[PDB]
Length: 139
Ligand SMILES: Cc1ocnc1CCNC(=O)c1nn(C)c2ccccc12
Ligand SMILES: [Zn+2]
Image (cartoon, rainbow, N blue to C red; front, side, top):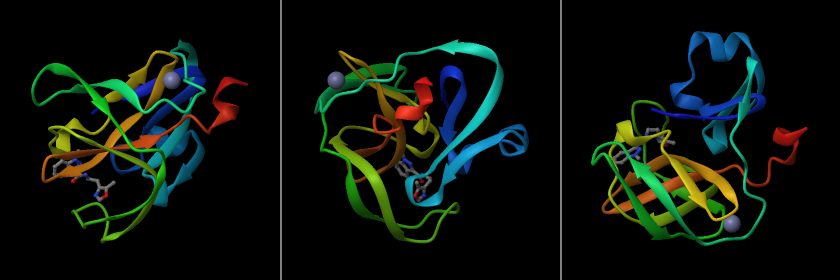
């Protein structure tokens, strides 16, 4: 689990969005596994605006943060789970690292701010849904 709080928005994995997230829907993209809902409280996370390929992510299944190198956001085939059939996921970044399903929502951060959230994984790889292109999160 996990979310990003920036301005009047909450960014979550679309497969983990709650009934309240869907009732306050701002934008969602199934191919990205992202959903953004509106909030009453102002959030103060900072979204990175950069092309970094190194950063640190939180891994709840190890209670640890790990530094990784990751690929630029791209269209990648992702195997099925109970939440989606196998399909191409867009704006996905991969790194070598540990993850389990419940690690979704863990934040990846570089020196500039939040890069994305854990979304996929397996075989020693962890995939992150990028948020750096969503310029509207700051306005
Ligand atoms: C976005 C997406 O695509 C398909 N199902 C999902 C959503 C469900 N995701 C997973 O099942 C999953 N997430 N991570 C980090 C893992 C690590 C090891 C094994 C499985 C997973
Ligand atoms: Zn950066």
